[PDB]
Each structure stands twice: as structure tokens, then as C-alpha cells.
Image (cartoon, rainbow, N blue to C red; front, top):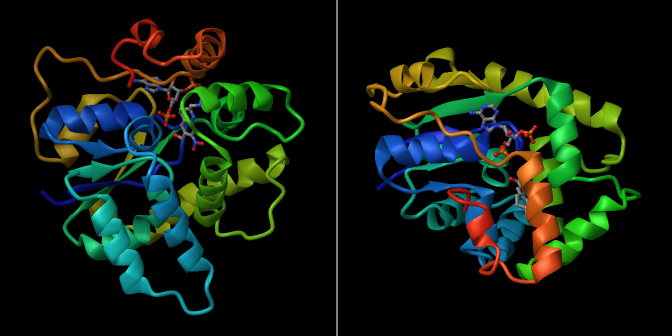
Length: 246
Ligand SMILES: Nc1ncnc2c1ncn2[C@@H]1O[C@H](COP(=O)(O)O)[C@@H](OP(=O)(O)O)[C@H]1O
Ligand SMILES: CC(C)NC[C@@H]1CCc2cc(CO)c([N+](=O)[O-])cc2N1
């Protein structure tokens, strides 16, 4: 197995649904942050080391390529942070892999990002996220890797992540740069709600008969998950309330 599809879209742009859609198309696993959080938390330190490598005056690109290849062994595709920030490196490693850019209205994205991925440092909800994440064993090292991977996608070192205006413009700039870098024939821009048709044509497959395009990972569902993790202090005791998600 080798990487066939590189998902360059940012978190909260429908990447979990695209993960599920690609697993339906190929019948093989697709990487996502959920893989890190719920299956392979040991990958957190590996990703951190690759992000740190990019900060060096002279980064070891072959160390990065091998780290990515090792991380993605057994996967047919990748989506979401932190992998999306490495889409250029992945394009080089997998010259035959096609690129997806999942995209959505920027104001809806920012709202979703603030409720799940990157709340403001003064937002009381941040403490609820953290208490719920402790049930999952997620600690401060995860937040550092996640934040660092987002800054790396935005190609900025010193950035005020609490400024909505700055995030909105980083969002647009990131999406614009993907379209500039990736050749058109190699890129599909998939807007939220687009469904199977464009995706399956791009990938040279038929539309899955009788199987609807996935619709998963809403911020309402993540808020409910946080509150149930805090209330019951166990993922196993609550997993039945979130069918088909993890
Ligand atoms: N088929 C679909 N149609 C419309 N929205 C979808 C969708 N699949 C996922 N989404 C939305 O995409 C966001 C999750 O993306 P990701 O998996 O990258 O984190 C959620 O937005 P909201 O948080 O606004 O509900 C989710 O509702
Ligand atoms: C339940 C909650 C309290 N924590 C678990 C959630 C699971 C979804 C999720 C997705 C991303 C990016 O897809 C990030 N991220 O980039 O940090 C964090 C989280 N966290």
C-alpha cells in the first residue's frame, strides 16, 4: 500500500467525512487526527519531531520524508492536521498521488475551529476541552503538536492565534496557496456538501451505489463528546452515544 490521495484541507473543513469517504472508495485506511487521538497517541511525539525539524536553519528533508513514510505505512490516504501541513513534502514523496482541498465558508470554519481545535486562551470552554481530553489521556504535548502543525501550515512563527481576523486571513491565504502550488489536473477542490460525484470522477471510480456521502464530526457532536467525557470519565462507557464516529 502507498499514498494515493493527499488531503491538504485544513481541520474543520470536512476532513473526517473525507477520511470515511476515501476508506469507502479504497477499502483501506486513511490517516486523520482521530487516528492519533483514539488509536495511536504515540504518533504525537513523532509528528512533533518532524515539525521541529522544519524550524531548523538547515532541515533534513530526508529525515522528514522517512518520518512521514513511516507514519503513513499502511494508509492509502491522509487528511487533516498535522499531515495537511506537509502536503508539499507528501507531493514530492508520492508524485502519482492526487491532492484534495476540502474547503468551506471561512466564517463557519473559524467558528468550528474555535469550538473544537483552537479556542481562545481566555475562553472558558478551553478548560472543558482539557478536562475531557484528560479522560482520553491527551495532555499538553498534544496541544503543542497541534498548535505547531497549524502554525506550520500558515508558515508563521510568531502569530497571535487569539485574533480571529488573523486566522481568517491565514485560512484564505493557505487555500489560495494550495491552488497556486498544485497543478490543476492534480487538484480537486471539494466544497462542503459536494458529495461523491466530483470526488469519484477525480479518482476514476464509480459512485458507491446505495452509500451516501459521510456527514460526521460536527461541533455539536464534539461538544456533546466533551461533556459526556467529563460526566462519565470513560470513553468506553459513552462510545455508544457516538455511533460510527470513531
Ligand atoms: N457531508 C457534510 N456536509 C456538510 N457538512 C459536513 C459534512 N461532513 C462534515 N461536515 C462538517 O465539517 C466539519 C468537521 O470537519 P473536520 O472533520 O475537518 O473537523 C463540521 O462542521 P461544523 O463544526 O460547523 O458542524 C461538520 O459538520
Ligand atoms: C473531545 C474533545 C474534548 N477533544 C477531542 C477532539 C477530537 C477532534 C479533534 C480534531 C482536531 C483536528 O482534526 C483537533 N486538533 O487539531 O487539536 C483536536 C480534536 N479534539
